[PDB]
Amino acid sequence: IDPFTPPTNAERLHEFHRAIGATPERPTPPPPELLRLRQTLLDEESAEVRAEIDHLLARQAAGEALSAGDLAPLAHELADLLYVTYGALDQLGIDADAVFAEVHRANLSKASGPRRADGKQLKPEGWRPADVRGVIERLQH
Amino acid sequence: IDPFTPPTNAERLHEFHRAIGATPERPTPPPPELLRLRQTLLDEESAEVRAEIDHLLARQAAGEALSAGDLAPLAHELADLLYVTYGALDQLGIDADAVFAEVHRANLSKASGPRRADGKQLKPEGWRPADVRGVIERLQH
Ligand SMILES: [Cl-]
Ligand SMILES: [Cl-]
Ligand SMILES: [Cl-]
Ligand SMILES: [Cl-]
Ligand SMILES: [Cl-]
Ligand SMILES: [Cl-]
Ligand SMILES: [Cl-]
Ligand SMILES: [Cl-]
Image (tube, rainbow over all chains, first blue to last red):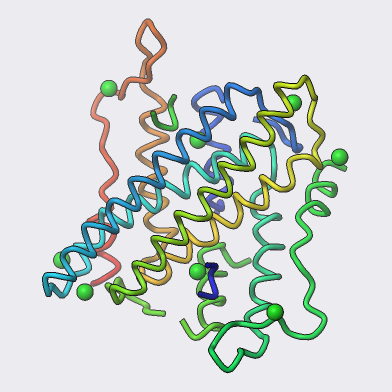
């Protein structure tokens, strides 16, 4: 499935990494041990988000109408996930906003296509996929 | 483990959801079926990120010095993950930037603590944890 089925937050992660001694201004591969760690951490944070969804689903199944406050733990974990995802991009010395803008361009464009009779989102004429490599090359040079 | 071990992107997701017919201005619980979907999608996108890390790790292990371009698929998947994470928060009608700011405050503050002899990050005096519930209540009211 897929989605169709003042400083920015990226800049905040740069501030954070400065604080913990952790980053490059241009795209730069990290040490293996650091990739490994990032992989684990993404793994863990996505697991916590999915667990909080499970709790809400169980409460809804029992018939509860959740309040705004009830959504806080999930919102907290989601933000934690943004943090470590932005963290990865910052660690890589990749401008997250530049890459995000290109991904957003392509997704928004795809959203403007027609739908199949069964409701599946189709691409519009002349749809242009996200060219993230082009963004990276641009940032590097 | 943990991290110690112009429109914003959140606003872009609101634009996207408008485009696909998908959102609330105040925190609002979603339908169960939609939570279920979001859970699956987070699951899948985090799996793809972790797979791209595996590929880079294998290349590094073989002795390669990765170029900036080599990082594009990982950067692309990371941005895809931001997209569906921001997507969740938007779906919930929760201002992602407000929640992120509070999580960032707490993380940056924790970073200012001393480290144990073994290098573990300790909290500073009077450290105040992220109060995401307070943010949610504020957004609701
Ligand atoms: Cl509900
Ligand atoms: Cl409440
Ligand atoms: Cl991080
Ligand atoms: Cl198509
Ligand atoms: Cl490398
Ligand atoms: Cl290259
Ligand atoms: Cl989404
Ligand atoms: Cl501590």
